[PDB]
């Protein structure tokens, strides 16, 4: 199946990927080509559907800002990701899948979004995550479930809705906290 | 009582005495009575050289004491200002040995000792203030421990931005903390 073309129904996303591959914007892309990529960065471009990204088995960095995707479900199997950034005023917690499969992830940034407390049980089993940025999510009020993260050292909750700090003592490796009320 | 109110106050620092005389409408070197010190509501000493605050212990009615960059030898004379509500002392030379134990500041609701050179020795000097509800310890790189502050019964707001705190165990024991400002290196 390595030579099979990949369905990338979003033309803007497909144009971006073709650019990385030195191809014209509407050219077809094989599974092998997707497997050759190491980073994807989508910042302030309109990408509504990330279908196709599940074939990018080797990307180590995925950086997304204000792309207005319907959801981010196709990232759930990207087991080689090390650094994941997803931001956007329209990114509510339903849009992000459970991330337990991101077994290489060391950095998670989901700042400047519209997350609520439900995001915490999607991100609290990441085995290697070292830093989490949850800042500028005003509806996040309870970060106690993050105590289950074995390697978390840095946590940013600036400008969230957190006003109860009980539980932070249960974080095994936390040594850098960024906090700012209101 | 009535006699004592007319007694002159020893204020050996001439810069401080001149400042106080300004507030009182007197010439810069005029003598100042105990009653006159008790008539003050605010004292702000900013970017003037005041080595010694002796005399300030008579300012029983001041509600705010604001001190920035005065290079005092120490701040001992403030220790008994039990009616003081807001205290700010800042300066790059202000180490914790220069601030007296503040447990006698029974009315204090606001403490700001930011932008200074404090270390963990300050903690036992400020952790039993009975009414303090906000403390700003920011920009003191040598403050590394917040645990002793759990003994403050009314503390709601704590600012430790740009300190040296890397261990947050004990924060769960603060009875009223509901606003935290924190930022590492």
Image (cartoon, coloured by chain):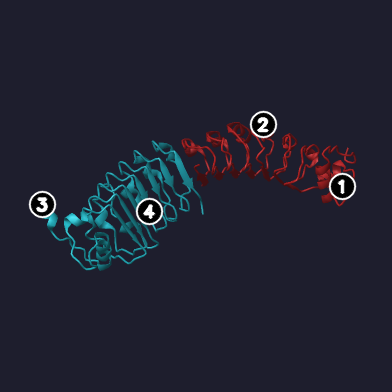
Chain colours: A red, B cyan
Q: Residue at x 83, y 50 (%)?
A: A19
- Residue A174 percent location from the top left of the image: 52, 44
Locate residue A75 relative to residue B112 in the image: left or right: right
Q: CA distance from mark 1 to mark 4?
A: 59 Å
**Is label 2 in contact with label 3 (beta carbons under 8 Å)?**
no
Please report the residue visible at 44 percent of the width from the left and 52 percent of the height from the top: B138
* SS for dot 3: loop
User: Which residue sits at x=90%, y=45%?
Assistant: A27
Q: Nearer the viewer, residue B135 or A52?
A: B135
Left/right of residue B152 with respect to residue A140 in the rendered view: left
Find the distance from the CA under tag 1 to the CA under tag 2: 31 Å
Q: Is residue A80 above or below residue B89?
A: above
Q: Which residue is mark 1?
A: A25
Q: Which mark is residue A94?
A: 2
* Badge 4 or badge 3: first in the primary sequence: 3
Q: How would you rate the neighbour count of disc 2 (Cα within 10 Å): few for under 14, some for 14-19, many for 20 or more?
A: some
* Residue B26 vs residue A175, the one in the foreground: B26
Chain of the residue that carries numbered disc 1 in the rendered image: A
Quadrant the N terminus of chain A occupies:
top right
């Amino acid at each position: 199946a390595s030579q099979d073309n990949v369905n990338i129904p979003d033309s803007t996303f497909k144009a971006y990927l073709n650019g990385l591959l030195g191809q014209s914007s509407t050219a077809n892309i094989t599974e092998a080509q997707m497997n050759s990529l190491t980073y994807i960065t989508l910042a302030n471009i309109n990408v509504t559907d990330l279908t196709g990204i599940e074939y990018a088995h080797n990307i180590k960095d995925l950086t997304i800002n204000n792309i207005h995707a319907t959801n981010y479900n196709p990232i759930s199997g990207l087991s080689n990701l090390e650094r994941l950034r997803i931001m956007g005023k329209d990114v509510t917690s339903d849009k992000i899948p459970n991330l337990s499969g991101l077994t290489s992830l060391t950095l998670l940034d989901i700042s400047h979004s519209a997350h609520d407390d439900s995001i915490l049980t999607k991100i609290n089993t990441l085995p290697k995550v070292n830093s989490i940025d949850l800042s500028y999510n005003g509806a996040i009020t309870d970060i106690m479930p993050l105590k289950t993260l074995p390697e978390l050292k840095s946590l940013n909750i600036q400008f969230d809705g957190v006003h109860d700090y009980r539980g932070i003592e249960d974080f095994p490796k936390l040594n850098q906290l960024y906090a700012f009320s209101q």
